[PDB]
Length: 244
Length: 254
Ligand SMILES: [Ca+2]
Ligand SMILES: [Ca+2]
Image (cartoon, rainbow over all chains, first blue to last red; front, top):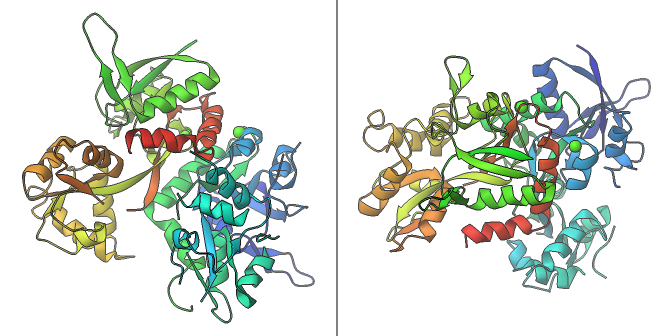
């Protein structure tokens, strides 16, 4: 079984450093890693993991993870990497292995992005100029809550843990990646958070443009999705089975 | 050049819009708009033709595919368009673009009832329900209702209703059959939500009303190793992320 280069980007609980002890090789865990193992175990290929030098997903030459692929320094790119047209142009993606959504972190009355966007008592924002910021903008100016969210968000934003922390010790809701948020919520030592749809796109696995693995990879991903296995894997990192 | 486009009639994905003496048929529909979007951007032209066997395609015991998927495997078509879902068995023999819309299972009911979900429909027996015998939905239901490793209470019920006599009681053998059974009798029809939705909307009497999540997606099938695969996905990604797709979607599902 040949060895493929896997480049990742830390993002809990998608890709995390599970082990890093002086004198030992770094080990990783997480939903994205599980999917890589499900594919490696079936297709019989092996691998070595390394993080994107800049800890960036990749923005237009290309930087970050996508860049590592465009410059053929990697073979696969496992991370909470969203499938977008620009990227799909420079690299090749599999099928989405999970749907990407925008969520809101609240502090222990709001129950939906709709309520969050009808009230003001609780200011709310995201990470300035980020993917989510642009998403709310783009939607907010279309031609019916997004418009009231943009009117609001567009002062109140910031740049990620800062937002997480705002909600914790102050009055503020944080709009951001829902899977990330949910994990943050579930695993909070004091259980001070609760989260609150739609899917504009999805998380993918990138391979270098014209890779011969894309096809069989997508097959295996679809099979894990349609068989119900993805869910067995999703519950491991996102279980509404207890704690908070 | 001109690309051969195969398809399967299905409302509102692909329908006949124009068919009048001494003229070539004209098709319309959500899937048709998407195809046009691709056609205009990549600037290619096509000629539409329907799946010889009116089926999306199943792996036949000869070791070859029939239906639409089959048209691509035998290189008779270049593009496959319709409410075709991206599935492992399929993607293994043909190349799919990224999904262009999500596929959810839904339920068609008759005005007067108050079933809020598949969960509810599952917890009552007063209104018998079902789907198409041996269809995709039939399988899914049987699969999740039979699984012992993870016993889904909902699907278990769903499953014992569907096969109440091995399928003779509540299953219809054609889409139209189940739809009409809801309207003229005591029956709930479990089918493709998008399809049932177009039917709910446009019912002349508004005697219908519909009600899950999605594990699949409808995709554009191309032939194994198609050169158009990558580029086709790029623009679908574009239409979705740029709210455009949502407009085409409000077109047939207002
Ligand atoms: Ca590409
Ligand atoms: Ca394929």
